[PDB]
Amino acid sequence: LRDLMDLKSNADSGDVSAQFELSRRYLNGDGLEQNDDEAIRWLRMAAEGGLPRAQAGLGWMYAAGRGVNKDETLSFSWYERAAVAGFPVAQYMLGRYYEKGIGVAKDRVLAKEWYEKAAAQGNEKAKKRLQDW
């Protein structure tokens, strides 16, 4: 009923959380018809709207070539925005990009910082490399 109507109305008003949830429903066909063009549209709007979880998911699509062509540079920039915001999964993915030189110049001094920030928030995969370092 109005559960989907309020969600769609909130996404139109500028709710980045509603835009991301609405993007997931279009992608998985949960509650709505499976529409890929609409799923990426709301994910773009939520990522550029400022949602870190949407910026990290949009950065993964550029890393895996899902929905868009595989671009390591655009994947690094989207993961960077979500990492600066404080998303723990994006901070781990960013430190991985710094040591490997994928999408950015290879660096060890900057890779340890994002490993130090992601592990400080409790990321489990960010402290395995931090001690095997």
Image (spheres, rainbow, N blue to C red):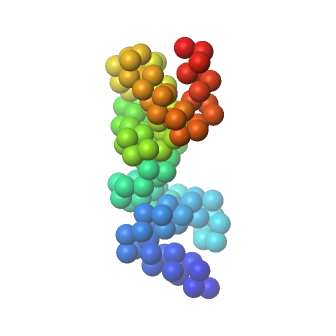
Q: Is residue 69 placed above or below 35 in the rendered structure?
A: above
> Please, which residue is most extreme toward the bottom here?
1
Compare residues 68 and 81 and report the one nearer the observer. Answer: 81
Residue drawn at 49 percent across, 51 percent down: 53
Residue 89 placed where, x, y %?
A: 53, 40
Residue drawn at 37 percent across, 55 percent down: 50
Residue 11 placed where, x, y %?
A: 44, 71
> Please, which residue is most extreme toward the front here?
120
Residue drawn at 48 percent across, 28 percent down: 116
Residue 63 appears in the rendering: no
Residue 122 placed where, x, y %?
A: 58, 38
Q: Quadrant of the N terminus?
A: bottom right
Residue 132 appears in the rendering: yes
Residue 128 placement, left or right of 41: right
Residue drawn at 55 percent across, 21 percent down: 130
Residue 76 placed where, x, y %?
A: 40, 33
Residue 3 placement, left or right of 93: right
Compare residues 1 and 41 and report the one nearer the observer. Answer: 1
Q: Quadrant of the C terminus?
A: top right
Quarter-of-image position of residue 111: top left
Q: Is residue 25 placed above or below 106 in the rendered structure?
A: below
Instruction: Tell me how many marks there are.
Output: 0
Q: Is residue 5 placed above or below 50 in the rendered structure?
A: below
